Each structure stands twice: as C-alpha cells, then as structure tokens.
Amino acid sequence: STGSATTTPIDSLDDAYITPVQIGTPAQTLNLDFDTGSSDLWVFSSETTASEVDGQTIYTPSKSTTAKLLSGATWSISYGDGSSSSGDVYTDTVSVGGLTVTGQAVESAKKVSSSFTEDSTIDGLLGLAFSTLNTVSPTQQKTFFDNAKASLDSPVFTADLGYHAPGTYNFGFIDTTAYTGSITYTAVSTKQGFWEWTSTGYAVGSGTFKSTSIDGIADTGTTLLYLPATVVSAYWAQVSGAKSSSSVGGYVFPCSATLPSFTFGVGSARIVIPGDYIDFGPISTGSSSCFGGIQSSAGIGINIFGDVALKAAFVVFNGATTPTLGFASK
Ligand SMILES: NCc1ccc(C(F)(F)F)cc1
Ligand SMILES: NCc1ccc(C(F)(F)F)cc1
Image (cartoon, rainbow, N blue to C red; front, side, top):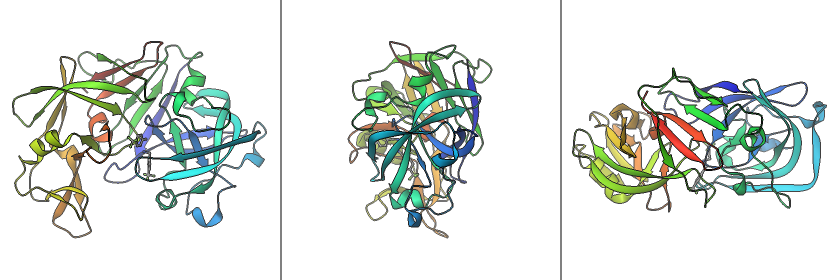
C-alpha cells in the first residue's frame, strides 16, 4: 500500500508545515507537524487543560468507536527548544493520505507548554524518527512509520517541502517525477535514534567547496539550519553588516542585503540552498534588521539540517533494515 498527503507552511516564513491526518472512527481530521526529529504522535485533545488550548482542533477519544485507552501508559516529552507536553495514551485508527494504521498509539496531551498553546495552526506532532526515542512508559510504542512499514510497497517515505508553497509527504513509493537528476544515498547512524548522517562539506556563494565532514540530523521538525560555528562564521562574513546578536540570539543582517547561496555535500553530490531561503525577515515588525536562517549549533550539541536545507531537496527516508538517506535536486 502507499499514501500521499499535501503539507502546507503555517505562515509566510515557512516556520513549520502542517499535514492533515485522520484519527478515529468516524475520522477526526487534525493538522499535524510531521517531525523526523522525534518519535511521539501526540495531539491536543478533550483532555488538554482548557486554558492551554487557543484555537487548536482537539481529538475527542470518547467520540471514536475504535479508540481504546492504553491502561497505565503515560508520556512526557521535552524538545530541544524547551518545548514540552505530557499526558496519557490511546490506541486508535490513524490514516495519512489514504494509508491506514490500526492500533496506532495516539498520545493525548493533558498539559502543553506555552509555545504550543500560542501556535493555533498546529494540532499536534507526528514523530518520524526511530521508535527507540518514543517516550511512552512503561511500554514503549512504535511510530506511525514503523507500524505501516510491513504494509508499504517499499519501506520508505519522502519529504518534498515547498518554499513558500505546499509540498508532499509520500509513504511507500518514490515519485520519480518530483526531482531532477539522480538520488544520492548516504549512510545513516541510528545510534542516537535520529536520521543521522554525514555531510561531505560546504560552499558559500560561488566560493570554493570545502571538503569537511559535518555530522548532523535530518529534521523536518526544525525550522532553521544549525551548523558548527566555523561554517556559520564563514557564511555570514560574506554578508555586509551581518553580526551575531546576543540580545536577538543569533546572526542578524540588514534587510537590504542580498544573501549568498549555501551549498552542502551529499557524497559526491551538491545541494544548493538559494540565498532567499535563508532570509527569515525582520526581527520585529518594522525593523530593518533581519534574522538569518543559518545559525550556530554550538549551544545545541548537534548539527541540524532543518527545513531551510531540506526544502531545497527531494529527501528519501529509507527505513530498510540498513537505513539510508537519499537527496536529489528539484
Ligand atoms: N525536531 C525534533 C528535535 C528537536 C530538537 C532536537 C535536539 F535539540 F535535541 F537536537 C532534536 C530533535
Ligand atoms: N522540534 C519539535 C517542535 C516543533 C514545533 C514546535 C513549535 F513550533 F510548535 F514551537 C516546537 C517544537
């Protein structure tokens, strides 16, 4: 079997992408943030503290004829940005673009951090990292991808994110019309539970390509590109007036500047990120200082190929027994 769903940016900056997901019987449609950096499927629900819900669509297990409470199970998650949420666990039927999984763990949020409350457009997350990272206790639960793998024509899903435009998540097949040239595959380490790989180097603008290994994770759930301080300093040195701002928390640049492209290596291939993808607009309404889409990973501990990098490519997440990541230009 296969599945295919359109994913849409939530705002004019591509801060996140939401994808409709059907849960329960009859279907309750929620718009979830597909996150290859985490492994929990959790939703705003009728059980969420009322003051902590501000416009989100909620899942109501009591109205689903296939929902079953998973007795004794709880979950609690903290994301790398300080976000957190927690609650209890149901199993229910979950469908993504025609692809159906029965008995999927649906984690019902009882408490959510403020950053989720303020995001009215995101009804929850759908984790797509490896199931070793799932936070359900005392019985760990499988992700939607792991549960569907057996039924898929091919144990893959692909991410085709748009620049200020809708895109596509496909499960079970590779759309050979959606990219140009060839797909370059590279090895993945699952030792930390992430889609972790090694980039072979980078270039700034039309500059010389620097061969150097950059280990990092492919994370659809992270907006920006986080790279080592040496690489990020080399990029922003090519932008007149750019500087790192402690009060803002990253590199800013004059909104009048033109940004150079950024190239990253995948084996012998090159993915080019156009400079316009790196502009995240004014730091405050009316400001002439703009926020950069490439930031240092020094304070994080790991390099993150977030949406800024991924939306420049067609990305294959190959969940075969030896997992690999594929990248193609588009
Ligand atoms: N998108 C999920 C996510 C968020 C943060 C991290 C960090 F910070 F631990 F790298 C990993 C994965
Ligand atoms: N990396 C996971 C993640 C994804 C989205 C959000 C947001 F946008 F809701 F704050 C927080 C954390």
